[PDB]
């Protein structure tokens, strides 16, 4: 047995066996993966050179060179844990502790990379079942011990990081509770241990003919319980609904008892989005759907960002909407084509041909997907394609199943490579009305570029649209520079374009009732 | 100015100017409406004779002057403070005012008001004009320790507005003068709406601005937005427009400890479905939709209930669903045709039942709304499934009128109560597996328990909602007056076929925190 915390990078993203690196002789960048031989990416080096000027090397510290204060001691608590849990279910070695300290924001990565580990948990517990979680929480309440559940640790808001250090603190790693317990194909529901990781969930559901359909960009390295405790957004939500809609019921172990769910109050909304501050979700009954009989993904190009946005609007107004759509601005478009694996070219050829008639400085890629019954897919496809025709979309063709849409999963791998070579990249996500969209998009990019160009520093910024609403979009900025304010600059300008409480007392009452001792992820 | 409570029947349903009545000496039953007087329904007398055996015995309700209501309690300091802020026309404590703010519209309610049994009246009715006036009232009620119970249409059937005890001075806050749409945002597709607005008034005001809400409970005509919110009522176009909680973007709620405003935890769900126990909703921002370009409603006949249910199942599995569907069992089908003042529908049904025994034939009404292209796609998909299940087409008729006859049914209850009869309902969710046997067994058990006694009884059902593995089955059962003997019998057989709490302590802390003195609809 290797635990997930050992298989996922302790100072970067995702699988330890998957990473970008440079190949001899010429410094070609290549993607190593566990299943496939290293795949060269011939254009990527040239792209990084163009946009941001040998690559300077800035390796992270090795784990033996990282100092972590010894764990606190709580002999009597630990004794009671020892009497119930197996030895392999309790860890306090350095690796264990570091990996249960940090999420995956840039702030986390920077800090772990330079060895700044100021508030590790004292102990990691890996329970096997709901009944073991109940015992652990019983004991944590009895002894006044802080508990912080962790799934993938992919959050970017510091949600798993211990805040204080007065009490003994335990990280409850949920990832050994990773079984689909049953699938009811008549109710179309599945009961699922929430420590399960995205691709493991989908693989186990597929075996029974079903799927969940929740697809955040962190799909590969985040868990069902994490999705539920954060209310994360998914990129097939137009078809399958938001996570809160997919959640029929779930069990929550709290300091004051297990809370069970089945015109009055709908109590699931008290726990969804609570970030481990109100107890530990253990098992969830989720709404599933039959594996779709038709799955079709298509790429398109638009002469400008304005044409794409226009199609986005018209598609939404026609009321016949794709399962997934994403629109890439010209910079993210160029990055998408610069990332063309020579191993493992037809659409790269269509893009090169297109950019002879239309300026590449302006060309946007769109990826559009459809799933469902053949008849439904056919109707939706034909409806959207007709709207695409009216907005000067140029078709790049299909490719086959879902893999046009699983290339967003590779992006965080690029961040690690950048961090290793004197660069950083960060993101800002905003909702913005169509009225302000093209003006904020243009102004944010020009402002950010010029602020670094005016100091003699290279800097690059792209954007994509991932979600559309009645009167707006979700706009996602990615911005990169060289290692030496930039967050504040993007934030100020987002606010300057309309881009995105007695309830405190209601929450306080819930929290004091549910968690009298404030042991649950105290904030 | 006439208040809504003066325009709605104080001892029956709906508009004081609309009712069924018996013409004399002919005995023909007729329907009066404020637009046309005494429209004969030539088949309805014969239907009533057939099913429940010809002179109708008369059982008139008591006149209001013959009804005793204990005088209001007095609370001079409280009332003095109210009198300083509220206009005299806003405060009522006459008998009519007290009676119409005591009872809902359940059978138990109607029975009690009709024999003059008024045990628990509020002491005062307050009709506020604005959010700011509700805030003052709730402040004053908390200061003086005065129970407050908000009311909309008073259409609920669970005793939700009926004062429970008489220790404290009790006020009914009639929301119905707060009945304006305050704005419509047609780019966002939201409207801000004072929640005392009645259903048809809401849709009329929204239509003026090119939008619609689409929430449609069977009580639509005489219930309010605030009632829908505070009860999470179900609506019969929800497959298309979503549930009331999905339509609710935000709202303001005035509580004994402050006004709770809405834009982690999604707090709206603490208040939706709270039945006035956690404060008073005053204004809501609701999701609206453009008035649809196509609205098409069709009728179909099926040779048996089993065929109809089959079509229901296969329609849902096809994933292409109508806006509204209802399936009427053979007894409710017969009632629907016997309720005839369209004449072409009767003609087709009469012809069909020459080929198929009428004792088995079920009517279905199926509607589609949306963009023409969407309506066309859904119509043609559903029509073809309907072919596979022996559905016979009755045609259309024009707009939504096929679908607004359900609004007239409670008017029939009043007429029955005036003629030595009663009628009640039980709704249940039930799996497709148990559906047909619960349907057959409930109907048969119910008639036999009365026929064994030498007493007429009639029972029908319809299906109003379908789910993945089930339906919502609605029973309507009627007999002669001589409720609790036959309701229990139904209640038991539903419980038989699988027909449709540490959270209590969560609720208690919310309620103790929000409403320390327990003035909000104390239970
Ligand atoms: C590259 C990248 C892409 C991302 N893309 C998206 C995206 O598209 N949409 C989106 O919303 N987010 C996205 N995120 C953020 C993040 O992945 C999501 O919030 C995700 O839901 C976190 O899941 P997790 O299993 O990693 O939770 P963790 O990081 O382990 O925990 C998050 C919170 O949930 C709590 N928690 C975990 N398990 C439980 C449990 N069983 N019971 C109670 N509380 C629990 C933790 O205490 C913590 O407060 C992204 C992050 C990265 C780094
Ligand atoms: C013939 C008939 C058909 C029906 N059909 C349906 C149906 O299809 N679907 C369904 O769900 N129900 C149905 N019902 C029940 C009922 O009409 C609904 O529950 C409706 O939502 C109640 O609305 P109302 O305005 O009359 O509320 P009321 O009866 O006035 O009040 C109901 C509850 O909500 C509270 N309330 C009212 N206003 C506020 C406010 N502003 N703030 C806080 N609390 C408030 C009251 O205190 C009470 O607790 C039906 C009832 C009848 C008689
Ligand atoms: C500098 C030119 C090369 C382009 C840089 C590639 C962009 C890398 C995107 C990585 C995004 C990972 C961040 C996830 C969001 C959470 O913090
Ligand atoms: C023999 C003809 C019978 C006519 C049937 C009329 C159905 C009347 C429906 C009454 C609506 C009742 C809903 C509230 C329930 C109260 O307890």
Image (cartoon, coloured by chain):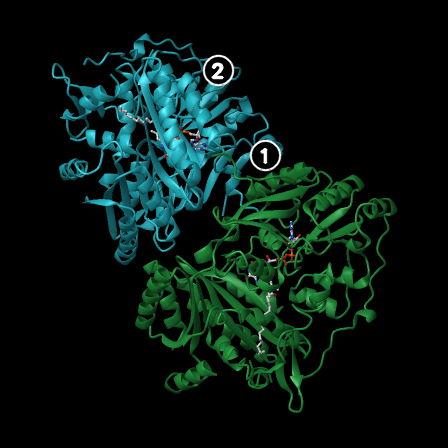
Chain colours: A green, B cyan
Nearer the observer, B132 or A469:
A469
Asked where in the image residue B197 lies, by quadrant, the reply is top left
Left or right of A422 on screen, residue B392? left
Residue B73 placed where, x, y %?
Answer: 47, 13
Return the chain for callout 2. Answer: B
Ligand 3's quadrant is bottom right
Q: Which label number is shown at residue B76?
A: 2
Nearer the observer, A424 or B178:
A424
Ligand 2 within 8 A of label 1's CB?
no
Residue B431 placed where, x, y %?
Answer: 44, 39
Nearer the observer, A193 or B126:
A193
Residue at mark 1: B510
Where A204 falls versus B82 (above or below)? below
Left or right of B200 on screen, residue B131? right
Which secondary structure lies at badge 1? helix
Asked where in the image residue B397 lies, by quadrant, the reply is top left
């Amino acid at each position: 047995h290797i635990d997930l915390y050992q298989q996922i990078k302790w100072n970067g993203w995702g699988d330890t066996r998957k990473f970008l690196h440079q190949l001899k002789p010429s410094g070609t960048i290549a993607m190593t993966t566990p299943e496939v031989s290293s795949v060269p990416l011939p254009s990527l080096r040239g792209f990084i050179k163009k946009e941001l000027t040998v690559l300077d090397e800035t390796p992270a510290l090795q784990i033996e060179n990282i100092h972590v204060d010894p764990p606190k001691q709580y002999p009597e608590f630990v004794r009671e844990l020892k009497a119930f849990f197996l030895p392999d279910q309790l860890k306090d070695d350095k690796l264990a502790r570091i990996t249960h300290t940090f999420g995956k924001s840039l702030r986390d990565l920077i800090r772990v990379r330079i060895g700044q580990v100021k508030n590790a948990p004292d102990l990691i517990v890996l329970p096997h079942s709901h009944e073991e979680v109940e015992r652990l929480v019983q004991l944590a309440h009895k002894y006044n011990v802080v508990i912080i559940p962790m799934g993938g640790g992919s959050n970017i808001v510091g949600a798993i990081e211990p805040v204080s250090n007065e009490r003994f603190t335990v990280s409850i790693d949920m990832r050994r509770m990773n079984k689909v317990l049953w699938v009811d194909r008549r109710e179309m529901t599945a009961c699922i241990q929430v420590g399960i990781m995205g691709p493991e969930l989908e693989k186990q559901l597929h075996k029974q003919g079903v799927s969940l359909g929740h697809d955040p960009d962190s799909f590969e390295f985040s868990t069902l319980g994490g999705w539920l405790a954060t209310c994360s957004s998914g990129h097939q939500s137009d078809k399958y609904g938001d996570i809160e809609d997919m959640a029929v019921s779930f069990r929550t172990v709290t300091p004051t008892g297990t809370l069970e769910l089945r015109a009055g109050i709908n109590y699931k909304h008290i726990i969804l989005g609570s970030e481990g501050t109100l107890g530990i979700i253990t098992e969830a009954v989720m709404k599933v759907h039959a594996v779709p009989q038709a799955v079709e993904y298509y790429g398109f190009l638009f002469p400008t960002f304005a044409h794409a946005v226009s199609a986005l609007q018209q598609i939404r107004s026609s009321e016949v909407i794709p399962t997934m759509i994403r629109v890439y601005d010209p910079e993210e478009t160029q990055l998408s084509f610069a990332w063309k694996p020579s191993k493992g070219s037809a659409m790269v050829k269509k893009y090169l041909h297109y950019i002879r008639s239309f300026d590449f400085k302006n060309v946007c890629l769109s990826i559009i997907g459809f799933e469902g019954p053949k008849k439904v897919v056919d109707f939706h496809r034909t409806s959207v394609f007709d709207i695409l025709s009216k907005n000067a979309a140029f078709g790049l063709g299909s490719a086959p199943g879902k893999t046009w849409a699983e290339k967003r999963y590779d992006l965080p791998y690029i961040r690690d490579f950048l961090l290793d070579h004197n660069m950083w990249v960060d993101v800002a996500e905003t909702t913005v009305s169509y009225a302000n969209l093209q003006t904020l998009w243009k102004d944010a990019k020009q402002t950010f570029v010029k602020h670094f160009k005016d100091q003699g520093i290279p800097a690059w910024i792209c954007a994509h649209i991932s979600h559309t609403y009645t009167n707006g979009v979700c706009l996602y900025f990615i911005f990169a520079s060289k290692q030496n304010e930039a967050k504040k600059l993007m934030t100020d300008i987002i606010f300057k374009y309309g881009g995105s409480r007695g309830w405190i007392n209601v929450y306080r009452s819930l929290k004091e009732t549910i968690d009298p001792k404030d042991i649950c992820n105290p904030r």
